[PDB]
Length: 184
Length: 183
Ligand SMILES: [Cl-]
Ligand SMILES: [Cl-]
Image: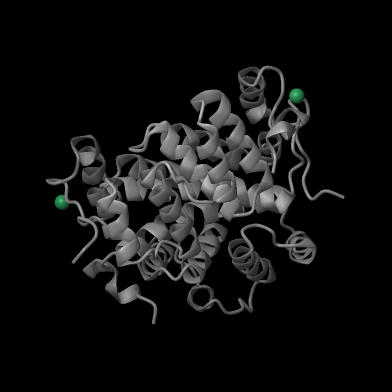
């Protein structure tokens, strides 16, 4: 049936057991199946953790980083990550429900032109593989983003590809603790 | 006018100056323009270097990792990265000419069924955002790769998207020092 084993602490390769233990604690007692999946390839698990940590340090706000991640997961057609990021945006960030709804639905953010442009720029980045074009780039800057922010969106898109494509490949089952955030 | 400044050591953000110094030395006295572009966003430059170092110790061989990078740069239409990885493959792997020519055009690899499937798998990942299908996934295992290798290909694709998409957006000028390798 499954292409991949979703690893537990018990079955994961020794050198990632300590990381899965950390993940489980940090998540209040469960391992999101994305991590259990990436445990199959410790360099892929390592990349996902490490880039996550670099990305937090980037030129975007934590809300803007979630704008990038949710929009990418929706554009990439990845249910697991739409659910995972929704849960993070609610519990970690307490994102306004209207912002969250818009991002999940890939529809306009009416309250905040800045974030709405960022969302739309992320879609264009993904579909064009970065060749967004003169007009899309100029609209990105007009609302106050910079060339640095542009490359930090690419960074988020790059991170989104690792987890969205991996979950797309595995058809990763959605943990019971994420099931309520599933799109829909 | 260009959308991005290509940074020098002098113009870069303070916290990446040392990275640029190290890059310049490693390349014998020049900075590849991707690096001067990424310098605009220190975290994107740092991700590119960090993930490169992780990818180069993954479950694929050095040849297989370049199969993935070049195939991805061709598929993503990124001219800079094709030249950058052709350079690395010639210098640092001594890749056979038939292999290198086939990667650079995404034409089949006739001498090597295993690398031909890897190359095809990579294209499928990129064109299907990972939904490569049961049959493409089975051909991948039957050739000798593992589920682990498959996620390490996704890893390579993700790293390629960072540099390919950035270079695509900037239309990064190709350094004179890389020109011999273009096309
Ligand atoms: Cl467990
Ligand atoms: Cl310089």
